[PDB]
Image (cartoon, helix red, strand yellow):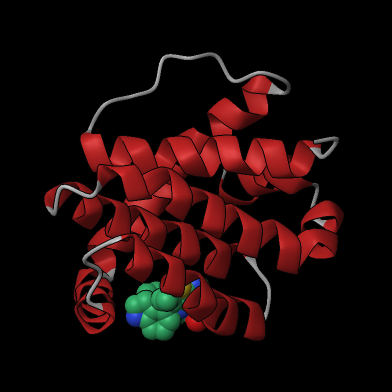
Length: 151
Ligand SMILES: CCc1sc2ncnc(N[C@H](Cc3ccccc3)C(=O)O)c2c1-c1cccc2[nH]ccc12
């Protein structure tokens, strides 16, 4: 509960996936360090949308292989993301890739009428990110470092 990095990471990732899936912006205010969270979500819309467009075939290929139909499938994706994401090197390129693939899957979840799985997917991505890359994120100045890196 006393973990600002986790709270802010979940807020950003949750909002991006939800707005990617529904096409609607969330109007609830951002709690603590609102400006940073706003700018981060703003950066994701530019860079994340970019990754999904530029790498559509690779994302569609991966989604087809994973065959997501339900909550059990979304649960097993987290195991995949740990192996895939956590075993490789650490940088904002791969972090945006992970979150962008998150958003790609979220749109699929809306397509197949499994919207209830989007919040659990966002929490699973947040947990992989902040659990496996804590020390890297803190050293990089967290979401302020993310905003500055993609300016
Ligand atoms: C679970 C899917 C995931 S999460 C994930 N998180 C971070 N990085 C990833 N990939 C980048 C390479 C990359 C870059 C852009 C588009 C595609 C790949 C990296 O490892 O450096 C992946 C992948 C992923 C891995 C391998 C093939 C893939 N094809 C579709 C997604 C995907």
